[PDB]
Length: 168
Length: 168
Length: 168
Image 1 (tube, rainbow over the protein chains, first blue to last red):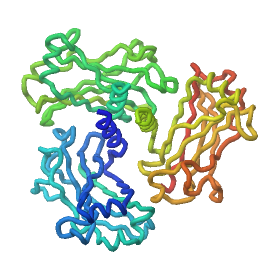
Image 2: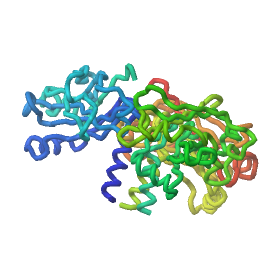
Image 3: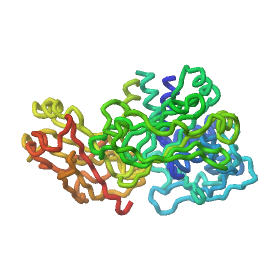
Image 4: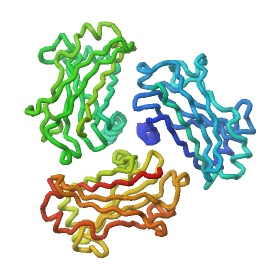
């Protein structure tokens, strides 16, 4: 109860309703090692929405990679979740998604973007809490970021997601 | 206090600040029977506002009717509540209000609208937590909705309120 | 924990993210006297932001004055706080700030505005929870408001802050 209430509070505190989400990941070094050790391979971000009563979404990241990026890259994925208002939304989900690793020197951000494969189960109306994630297995080489550079600063990185709202 | 905190959280989670409110009512059948049985004739929706510091409002619904619609219609009412910034607002409340029962096939929503009766106590600056509710006693026949149709889907209905912001 | 969670909830409830904040100060008479008695010289307002992930700011008011306004004026100051996303923001803080004491008769509001002194310690990237406050020592004579007039009504006053978003 108490713990479950704190959770709702944190989720409410991180949520946004305009399709733009910024995820600050503090304690980067520790989490990065917990991933390398396979103790905590992935981390989910809090949920965010395309509009006040729009699609519910979240991100999933592997600090030491997944799939073709395992052990060599930071893998970042987008997840369509079951939203409270899904019955009012058009399905399958078909909004362009842009994902970024922010350069804290704003000189060169890592960026990738994709248009949902309407035939994939990842974008159908959610039956479970979350649909199968999809995104960027090779989002960023562990060396480009992590190592040093300008992506990690004061032991934290910022991930940014932009869900295009065309048609909504 | 714990229970009181949960309530505030849930209210904050539902609040909107642009005059548009979508109220999803799950467990329709059960609440519908609680209404027919006379155990819980009415339900208040969480509060929403015309602006970040505007009028505070909520909805009141009778799943089995009230007044001229008792036992035959779904009665939907609008409620002007005592807001924390009422001293900065113009009174009496004078914004056009639109109420809707959403068709979950978007085939044809039930809609009605009204201009507040400036001389009614329902729209004067609140002295109590809530002014006397007013709205639509004959909003929707129990048969048009409930029965089946496209308003009730997966045992839930969606009510939508839109407060016109002209002059604010 | 319990009180900690309530505090978090109260903060979230008061925050805004568009650079506009309205601060309602109730129990004016009592707090006014506590300031006069030197028991509680100043009060801080809840935090608000320039954007969803922008600068974090709050206000600091002296109901019985501070500095050149001590004992004769209401002193109102602006505070740049350490925000969770300062790494992503440009420093020093350089947005125009407008502060107002609202006339609850909307006939004559007290207003002042300033463009940050970029060389000031008050606008550099925060090292501590709060930077040195800056603002209006002689914002409003204790007599103009307090005494009576239209600023204090039903034992409450409203302070409003508007942070210009040009460049953000």
